[PDB]
Structures are given as structure tokens and as C-alpha cells.
Amino acid sequence: DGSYLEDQDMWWFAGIYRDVYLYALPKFHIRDVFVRTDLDENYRNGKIFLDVEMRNLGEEEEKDLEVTLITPDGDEKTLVKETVKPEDRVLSFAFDVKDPKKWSAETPHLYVLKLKLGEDEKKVNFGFRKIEIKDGTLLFNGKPLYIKGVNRHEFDPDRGHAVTVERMIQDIKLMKQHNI
Amino acid sequence: IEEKTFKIFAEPGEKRLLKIPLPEMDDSEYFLEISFSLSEDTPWAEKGHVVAWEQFLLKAPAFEKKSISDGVSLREDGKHLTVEAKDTVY
Amino acid sequence: IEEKTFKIFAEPGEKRLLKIPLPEMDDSEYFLEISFSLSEDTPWAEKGHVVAWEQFLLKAPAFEKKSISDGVSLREDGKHLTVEAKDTVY
Amino acid sequence: TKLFVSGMPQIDFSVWPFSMEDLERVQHISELPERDFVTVNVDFRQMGLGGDDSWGAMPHLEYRLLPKPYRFSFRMRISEEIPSWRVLAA
Image (cartoon, rainbow over all chains, first blue to last red; front, top):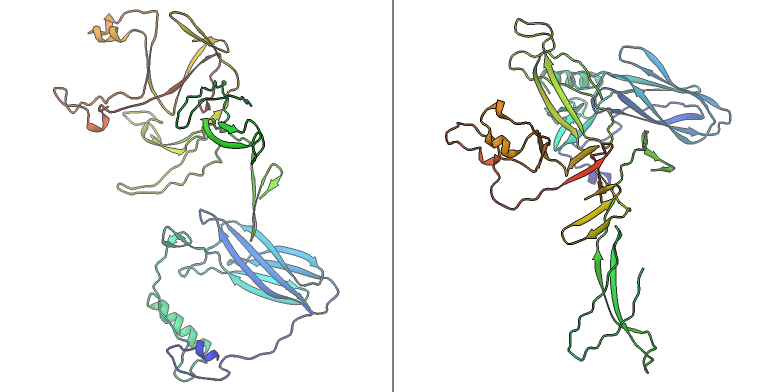
């Protein structure tokens, strides 16, 4: 019945066409992370808005939560360091950052959040950038944005939908070398 | 603020003038009501039953605009904006 | 209430942007003035001579309307009407 | 004593140490007489000066008071201190 919503103009294939794996987490672990940014009216200073969802499956003892910010240069800063009792809860934080390096297609500067709850460790890449509509005009970090785009199907002439990282890198470098 | 009784003589179809002395007025809104009621009991109703009334604006109010000097605070987070003034939080 | 010096680099014919950080404002009227003056003495004029200026309204005022409660007296005679309020007679 | 005038929201004004009749009569600076009063003018507007030439040219159309209905108001107070121009009676 799923096939009635998969009528794309393309080849009908089938099978386990992407990776399969097993992993293990502690009884008390981070289930989910939502990191969002805002920029001021001069597109100068930034804010980080962080939601951390925790999940407990039979833990009783209290664990330590640490959140570290790594800059594009490589400098580190502790944002959060606290003790949390084991329970199902969403923790929310808001931090200020001065003159952050902004992400664009021309200049892709990435910050890293490192999150650790007991022995559970995760990392997320994020950038400071803002998309908005002002009087019918599309703005990106305060500048008018022109979309110079292409539609791409995830396709390979030998492997079908089961495309490799080497082929993905070839596609991107070719796109940028032709001003897309 | 003021009430007064009167009697007026008018035959079927006649128009008669009624003169009402007005007080000096401040910046409030003033309305006049004129009514007619039963002088004595009838088979269908009691003394004081109103049969007719009309109302009129005498004077519109004078609105006051005051300059506020006291301050307001603002706190932002990820989901809420909070605004504090005196002992109310929005 | 606020003064600040600056320097701007612009060649003949060029347009350049100038960003001015504004304070929080009360119910008063606010005007901005931007001027350019001689950095040092010339043969025709001294340091500080203004060569160009322009002014702009930042914020219109908020007018206040107050309700007066105090009274006024009036005396008529054959030639004059006299009106008294506080310690002035018209 | 201060004589204070405020616009609703603006006026034009002038103050002279002689009469309008004195100013219209004398043809040299030396002949302007000594007087024991000040003439005060409080105006809605005056027509432009013009000067495209001085032997027939008029002020431009947008600086003339063409004959249509006009209105104008101001507030006056006589006291010992300058009150707030931004505060009026309701």
C-alpha cells in the first residue's frame, strides 16, 4: 500500500539498499537533541537554543551531564555541567555567543556540540545562519539570496539506489566547479 | 444625578415643546432619558408602568492621555517571551 | 544628550553606509544631526569649520491631555466681560 | 513673569521693538524709532519670499495661501515658570 505514495518518475527497484548495524547505549541515555540558532538585527551576535531529551530504562543512580562547545578555530568552552536524577525529561538551555563565524555555501564554518551523560557520548555539527522573508524578498544572513540549483536523483548505473560516499563526493565537487 | 416629574397637555396628533434646565457639566459623558408612565392602576397594569421612553446624548466625554514613566522588563528563551510590569507577567 | 565622532572613507562619487546605535527613548521628540568639519587648518578657514550637515526626525513625541477640575468665574457689565482663573484676569 | 505660547502642534512667530506701521514707513536703518513696547506675531503661515526675479516674478504655487477656508489654534499661559509644551487641557 506504501507503493501508492512512491510513484516517482524513476526505476522501480527493491531490497535492503542502505546499511544495517547493531549498537548499545547505557540504561539512562540521551534519546534526542534539537540545536537551533538566532542572530541579532545586525547579524552580529548569536544565541544557541538547546533541547536535550533523556530516557530511563531501569537506572536508579544519578549521572553527570556535560555540554562542551568547540569553535571552528578549535577552542573549547563548557556550557553546562550538572548532576541529573534518572527520569524521562526534556531539558532546555539558552546561551549567548559574541561575533560567531556564520555558515554559508560560500563559507561553511561549523561549530561542534559534545554531549556526555554518564558513559553515553554524542556529537552534533551546527552553524549560525538565518533564513527569512522581508517584504516578499528571500534573505540569508541579511542578504538577498538567488537559488542557482539542480534536482538530483540518488542513482548509480551499476548499483541503482545503493550509492557510495566516493560517488557522493564526485557529485558535489562537480556541482561546485559549475557554479551550482 | 438629577430626576424631575412633569405633566404635559397634548390632544391626539398634537406636538408640544418641553424645556429642561441643564446643569453645568464636567469631563464625564451625560445622557438624558424622558419617560411616560400610568398615573393610576388600570385593569391590565399597575401605577408606574412605563408606556413610552426616549434617550439623547447631552455631552460627549473629554478623554485623558497620561505619560507613563515607569519601566518594563523582557526575558527571551527558546519557546517563550516574558514581559513584566508592576506585579503582572505576560 | 549624546555626541560621537567618526571617520568614513569614500572616493569622489562613492556611497558609503553609516550605522548609528540608538538609545531607548521616552515620550520626548528626538532629532539626529550628522556633520562633517575640517580635520586641520586650511589657508581659508580654521580646524572645526563645518562644510556639510543634515538633520532627521528619529521619534515624534507622545502628547499628554490632562482633565482640569478647578473652576472659572465670569462677571458681565455694560461694556466688559471679565473671566478669572487662578491669579489671571482676562 | 513668562508669557508662554505652544503650537497645536506648531506655529511661526516674530518679535519687533516697533509697530508694523513704523516698519512700513521708514526707508533707512537710521530712522527706525525708539518705542516702549514689543510687537508679537503668532502665525499659521506667511506666503513665500520668491525672487526668481524682482520685476514681476511671484513665489511658486506651492508657497501661496490661495483663498479657501483655513483654521489655526494655539495655547497661551502667563506664569512664573515655563510649563511642558507636551501637556494640554483635555
